[PDB]
Amino acid sequence: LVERLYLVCGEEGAGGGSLVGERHFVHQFKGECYFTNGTQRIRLVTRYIYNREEYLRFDSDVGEYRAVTELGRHSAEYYNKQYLERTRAELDTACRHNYEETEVPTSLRRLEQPNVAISLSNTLVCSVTDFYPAKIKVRWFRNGQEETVGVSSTQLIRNGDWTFQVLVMLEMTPHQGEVYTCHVEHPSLKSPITVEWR
Amino acid sequence: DIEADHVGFYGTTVYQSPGDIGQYTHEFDGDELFYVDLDKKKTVWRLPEFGQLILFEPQGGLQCIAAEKHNLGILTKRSNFTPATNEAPQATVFPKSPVLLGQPNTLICFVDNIFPPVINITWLRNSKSVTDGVYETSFLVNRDHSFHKLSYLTFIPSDDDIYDCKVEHWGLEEPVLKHWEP
């Protein structure tokens, strides 16, 4: 069993001791790995956040921790002396490892075929549902001509269950003889999907 | 803001006081990989197939929570005890697949602008509580450091579908009852 790794949360050089006890106080940590063209370029950004204010950040493009706001002024010096070398190393030991050893065999290989159906309500709606990953191309055709004006589209909707949907609408008016088709291309499909509506 | 082909969150952590509430999750391309059940010390995969050959040692999330508890104590004092601002969450409910009479489907309640990350999302049908089979995500991070969460209710579309998603949050004077418009 190969292993997903994580970005370690660095501690303030504190020691603390103050107590808060309808008031609440929130702290966040975010360890972010950005990948482009495989692992050919990786950018690691770690964020330390008090309530909603990011006050301290490591950015591998920058090379060290920097205070993002005044609230982080004292934090940066301490994090650079205590955690800089191991944070730098995590670009390889956490970001690259996770992509190459765990995303390549799971997330990046995952494929789910879109379902495609056409409904009226005028507006023809091509409902393109339950696909993964996000890359998709949906086009409306009105008797053989790809439509441009009159087409609108929802944002790509994240279902939260590792599928997406998008609804692609064509403003039109029904007439006895016309055919309409939505064409869908997605990396999961052996051949593009066409659904006709009359 | 930062453009990339893919982004992993290998370390999403939140902790709050008082109440001692927090979570630890991983995400890939904005979808939840797992959360760590902190008290049971175990990784809970968003989809069960994720952990069949890959492991995540739950100690990693325990370390991050411990560090964030410590970090919160420092920053709370440094801020002169500036409290979080309660936001008003926003709910939308929509179906997973096109609605067709008699054909199995899922209603999704998408709740955004969540802060702090403590909330109750529940479902009603014909204004009666429905809890069987309901699933909800962890708190998923937003770029502005608020959260969103989704709840899911399996259903069979019918003649008079009356479904509501109820959201309770400290940032709301009254619970929002978000009606699904079929």
Image: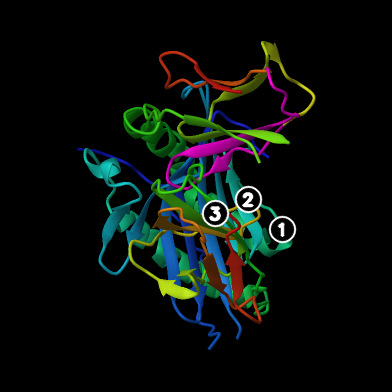
* C-alpha gap between disc 1 and disc 3: 21 Å
CB atoms of marks 2 and 3 within 8 Å: yes
The residue that appears at 50% across and 46% down in the rendered structure is: B99
Front residue of A194/A77: it is A194
Q: Are marks 2 and 1 on the same chain?
A: no
| Mark 3, residue position | B141
Chain assignment, label 3? B
Report whether B168 appears left or right of B38.
Answer: right
Q: Which residues are magenta?
A: A152-177
Secondary element at image label 1? loop
Report which residue position mark 2 lands on. Answer: B143
Is A153 included in the stretch rendered in magenta? yes
Q: Residue furthest right?
A: A149
Residue A81 visible in the displayed image: yes
Please, what is the three-letter code of the amino acid marked with disc 1?
A: Thr
On residue A194, the disc is none
